[PDB]
Image (spheres, rainbow, N blue to C red):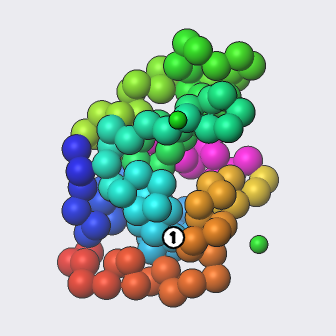
């Protein structure tokens, strides 16, 4: 599913990401824009051979099991394919674990390089929340 910007914002807010660990909803929408273009089906190989899955590009080295990543820890205890569903529940629950890993949203290099230090509130402008 390709979410609208505010449609994703509303889903993330419902699932409790708004201000989760101090990260405002605009941070999560900004990250999803640049990780997946709001597309739950997005998949992308990483340099280390793992693959990133779903709206927030959750990787198969630490977080989900894709059957083809040596060293997979599957800390979210989920097949990576479940992160591609039109329902973002699994991606949100796993992202809450990722953002708790010590590095906050710097766990997503795209957030660090494209969202951090910008006007991320702009990503929820016009949203009816
Ligand atoms: Cl590739
Ligand atoms: Cl930095």
Can residue 71 be seen at all in this image of the molecule?
A: yes
Can residue 77 be seen here? The reply is no
Coordinates of residue 69 in the picture (x, y in percent)? 64, 19
Q: Is residue 126 above or below residue 115?
A: below
Residue found 47% across the figure and 26% down from its top: 80
Query: Which of the four quarters of the rendered structure image does ligand 2 lie in?
Result: bottom right
Q: Residue 31 at x, y = what percent? A: 50, 62
| Residue 14 shown left or right of residue 97 in the figure | left
Quarter holding the C terminus is bottom left
Q: Position of residue 49 (x, y in %)?
A: 66, 28
**Residue at disc 1, secondary structure:** helix
* Residue displayed at 28% across by 67% down: 5
Which percent across, then down, holds residue 47?
68, 38
**Could you tell me how many numbered marks the image carries?**
1
In screen coordinates, is 105 left or right of 102? Answer: left
Q: Is residue 129 left or right of residue 111?
A: left
Q: Is residue 63 above or below residue 22?
A: above
Q: Is residue 59 left or right of residue 125?
A: right
Above or below for 92 versus 78: below
**Is 96 covered by the magenta stretch?**
yes
Instruction: Give yes or no for residue 91 being in the magenta stretch.
Output: yes
Q: Residue at x 64, y 69 (%)?
A: 113
Residue identified by numbered label 1: 27
The region drawn magenta spans 90-101
Which secondary structure class fits the magenta region best? helix
Can you tell which quarter of the image residue 103 is in?
bottom right
User: Within 10 angstroms of label 1, few (less than 14), some, or many (20 or more) residues?
Assistant: many
- Residue visible at 66% across and 67% down in the picture: 112
């Amino acid at each position: 599913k390709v979410f609208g910007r505010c449609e994703l914002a509303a889903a993330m807010k419902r699932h409790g990401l708004d201000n989760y660990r101090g990260y405002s909803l605009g941070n999560w929408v900004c990250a999803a824009k640049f990780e997946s273009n709001f597309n739950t089906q997005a998949t992308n190989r990483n340099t280390d051979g793992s693959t990133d899955y779903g709206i927030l590009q959750i990787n198969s080295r630490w977080w989900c099991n894709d059957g083809r990543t040596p060293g997979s820890r599957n800390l979210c205890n989920i097949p990576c394919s479940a992160l591609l569903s039109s329902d973002i529940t699994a991606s949100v629950n796993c992202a809450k674990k990722i953002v708790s890993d010590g590095n906050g949203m710097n766990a997503w290099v795209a957030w660090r390089n494209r969202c951090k230090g910008t006007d991320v509130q702009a990503w929820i402008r016009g949203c009816r929340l």
